[PDB]
Image: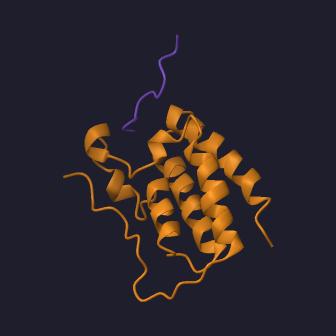
Chain colours: A orange, B purple
Amino acid sequence: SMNPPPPETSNPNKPKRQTNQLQYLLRVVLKTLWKHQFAWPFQQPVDAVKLNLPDYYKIIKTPMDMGTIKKRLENNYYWNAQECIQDFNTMFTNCYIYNKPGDDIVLMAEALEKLFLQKINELPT
Amino acid sequence: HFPKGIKQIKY
C-alpha cells in the first residue's frame, strides 16, 4: 500500500529516566495540542491511502505524528526534552514541505505550531 | 500537488 508501518515507540534497552521537562511535555504541551480543534489530522500517521497521496512516503523520509510522540513519551523513549521537541519540529516540517503553502492543513499546522512554541517557552529549566 | 483537501466546509 501507500502507507508504511508506523514509527517505533519503544527505545530498545534504554533505562528509565523521568524528568520534570518530560512530564511537562506529556501533560502540558502535548495535552494542549491534542485537545485543540485542529489536532485531528496530526493525531495519527498521515494516511496516504485514504487521502490519496501516492508520493507522501517517498517525499517524507521521517514520518512523525502526535500519536507517535504521545506513545514515545509514555514509553520514556526520549532521553531529554530536546529529542521530543525535535519530533514535534519534524512533524511540522513534514507538513510544510509536502503541502502547498496556504492549504488548510498548513494553516492548521501553523496554528498548532504557534501554540506549541508558546508552551515550550514555559518548559521547566 | 496531491492536496489533502479541506478540513472544514466554507459556509
Who's the residue at 32% across and 38% down the image? A51
Q: Position of residue A31 (x, y in %)?
A: 60, 51
Outermost residue, top direction? B11
Who's the residue at 45% across and 27% down the image? B6
> Residue A13 is drawn in which quadrant?
bottom left
Please tell me which residue lies in front, A60 or A29. Answer: A29
Please tell me which residue lies in front, A119 or B1. Answer: A119
Count of numbered badges drawn on the protein: 0
Q: Is residue A101 visible?
A: no
Q: Is residue B5 left or right of residue A70?
A: left
Q: Position of residue A60 (x, y in %)?
A: 41, 58
Residue A36 sits above or below residue A71 on the image:
above
Q: Position of residue A21 (x, y in %)?
A: 70, 70
> Residue A26 is drawn in which quadrant?
bottom right
Who's the residue at 59% across and 39% down the image? A36
Q: Is residue A120 left or right of residue A56?
A: right
For the C terminus of chain A, which image quadrant? bottom right
Q: Is residue B1 visible?
A: yes
Who's the residue at 49% across and 23% down the image? B8
Outermost residue, left direction? A1
Q: Position of residue A70 (x, y in %)?
A: 50, 60
Residue A98 sits above or below residue A51 on the image:
below
Please tell me which residue lies in front, A124 or A8. Answer: A124
